[PDB]
Image (cartoon, coloured by chain):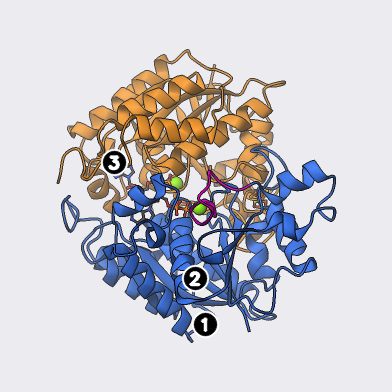
Chain colours: A orange, B blue
Amino acid sequence: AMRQCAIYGKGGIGKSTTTQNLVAALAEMGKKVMIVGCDPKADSTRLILHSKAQNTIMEMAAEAGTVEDLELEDVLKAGYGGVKCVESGGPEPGVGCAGRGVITAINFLEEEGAYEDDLDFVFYDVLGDVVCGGFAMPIRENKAQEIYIVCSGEMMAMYAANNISKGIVKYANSGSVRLGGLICNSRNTDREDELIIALANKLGTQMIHFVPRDNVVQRAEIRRMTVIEYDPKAKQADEYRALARKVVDNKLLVIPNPITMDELEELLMEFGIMEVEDESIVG
Amino acid sequence: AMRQCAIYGKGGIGKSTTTQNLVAALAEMGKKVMIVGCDPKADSTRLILHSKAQNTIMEMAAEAGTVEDLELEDVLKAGYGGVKCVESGGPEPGVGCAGRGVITAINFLEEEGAYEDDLDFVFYDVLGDVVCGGFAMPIRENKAQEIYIVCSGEMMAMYAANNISKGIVKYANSGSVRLGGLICNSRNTDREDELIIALANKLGTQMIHFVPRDNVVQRAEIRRMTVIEYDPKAKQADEYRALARKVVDNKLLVIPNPITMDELEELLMEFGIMEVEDESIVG
Ligand SMILES: Nc1ncnc2c1ncn2[C@@H]1O[C@H](COP(=O)(O)OP(=O)(O)O)[C@@H](O)[C@H]1O
Ligand SMILES: Nc1ncnc2c1ncn2[C@@H]1O[C@H](COP(=O)(O)OP(=O)(O)O)[C@@H](O)[C@H]1O
Ligand SMILES: [Mg+2]
Ligand SMILES: [Mg+2]
């Protein structure tokens, strides 16, 4: 068996940091994992590969001739813990559709047998600011059964979580795409954990983990590593191991109940997030 | 004469707060302004209209029959300082193209003569996480001559600024779309002003204003107002008046020089943004 998972969320919310660290923790447990980068930023695999980034399927297809010309053994790259890595890429700004590379990449990986019987997990790291074109494809075409949304007490982050949830509902008449959980990537603000638990409950899911804000992430990433590899003893390494454990153990996969903007505003005001003057722990 | 301006930037960076406050300051000066919301979040006019939000052209066209059926006098709404307001709207998550409403809205406003000879400014408030479909239309179809990008020391915010700049370059062989400036929306971090000045210089533009992080924004917005209307004496009201003055006075409109991710990473490391442990002013 293999579990096809996607990590969605607004830009800069922590999808790639959270995904690569979660996947490093899964590899540390003995899981076989593939990361498929589905964000035009195309740095979703750099911490596994110890690299600047990774050349994209779009770039490699352009050099080879066509995508069907590429070899999977030439495309996939293995890094920390034997984690397999691939980047979709996408057109330059202002051209066609920012998500078109995701469609090409997932279809190529499926056609060429990348989904080996011994993989335990695939994680798609997907841009979530718009739910359309190739960014919607993992939901619309039933590629990722378990959606985990990285979010925070930020209105935009919660709005994005709600829109991804609407996408899941839209396509629920076929396939098996479900919301698996919210991951709160901390803004170091009072009652943020309570806020995302409350949002999860309104959507019908759970807050699968509260990831603290820890500057060790900046120190590991300057060195192109996951915290798991950079400092296995770090407090934050144990946080990603806890998230990985709860993902492995998770059995709650729902058709979510999207909320109104009235409900989103009520949550923010209920937990006093917009009335906070300073961080929970200054420094 | 009228100046067609667009405010771009990543989600949650401060486009709508900055645009509505800038435009309130322009109205306070005696300028005639229209805001065109080009973000599916569709809350780009609520602080001018004292409102929850505004019904969108897509919503109103669906109720009327077709868009060509709508009357401009029924669509535009005036709020604080006589500022005229309209929202594009867009399809539900998972459908067609998130930006399609922007195309319909701008074409309708142009056809129906919304661009009255007495308007001094139009501001499009445009989603900037992807530069494609209707989100690219204001650049591709020469609708906004002056692009101002709201950004911060956040890598994602600078990446977005660079991608919007690539879009401007892509379409520079026709029309007159130019980069007018970066607006730094402060994260209360050391040397962030210096970082965005340095980014502006590499792109060939300027940092037109450094907008401080001020919790008075949360207090005004809870009451559905700009800071300009909520508290005309506020320190932050004078910040938006300074931005408005520099926009009125700006004559630097360039074809930008997009940078590499290497250059973006070099900027972050040069100004020590990722090595900071606490905010510049705690609290
Ligand atoms: N838990 C965390 N603590 C500290 N910094 C974090 C944490 N999670 C993410 N970051 C930082 O936040 C920024 C954005 O994270 P990233 O995963 O690249 O976002 P996305 O992939 O959603 O655009 C990066 O600078 C990253 O190092
Ligand atoms: N200068 C500022 N100081 C304090 N809060 C701000 C400031 N600018 C924006 N905000 C807040 O940041 C959030 C996002 O701003 P918004 O303009 O809605 O972003 P966007 O339109 O780019 O998605 C809102 O909660 C807004 O009140
Ligand atoms: Mg990423
Ligand atoms: Mg907005």
- Residue B51 falls inside the magenta stretch: yes
Q: Quarter of the image holding residue B182?
A: bottom left
User: Residue A83: image x %, image y %?
Assistant: 42, 35
Question: Residue B114 versus residue A81: which sits nearer the camera?
Answer: B114
Q: Is residue A27 above or below residue A217?
A: above
Which of pointers 2 and 3 indicates the residue nearer the eye? 2
Report the disc number at residue B88.
none
Mark 2 — on which chain does it sit?
A: B
Disc 2 element: helix
Instruction: Report the magenta residues as a range.
Output: B45-54
Residue behind mark 2 = B27
Camera-side residue of A156 and B47: B47
Residue B84, x across and y down, in percent? 60, 63
Q: If the image is split into quadrants, where does the N terminus of chain B sit?
A: bottom right
Label 1 CB-ligand 2 distance < 8 A:
no
- Compute the Cα span from label 1 to label 3: 40 Å
Label 3: which secondary element: loop
Q: Amino acid at mark 1?
A: Val
Q: Which residue is mark 3?
A: A275
Relative to B248, B155 lies left or right: left
Q: Which residue is mark 1?
A: B254
Disc 3 crowd, CA 10 A, few/some/many (<14, 14-19, 20+) = some
Task: Kindly report the distance in space between the C-alpha atoms of the residues bearing marks 2 and 1.
Answer: 26 Å
In the depicted view, which residue is nearer to us: A233 or B58?
A: B58
| Mark 3 C-beta to ligand 2 under 8 Å | no
**Can residue A124 be seen by looking at this rendering?**
no
**Element on which disc 1 rests:** loop
| Chain for disc number 1 | B
**Looking at the image, which is closer to me, B87 or B74?**
B74
The amino acid type found where label 3 is placed reads: Glu
Crowding near the residue tagged with mark 2, few <14, some 14–19, many ≥20 C-alpha atoms within 10 Å: some
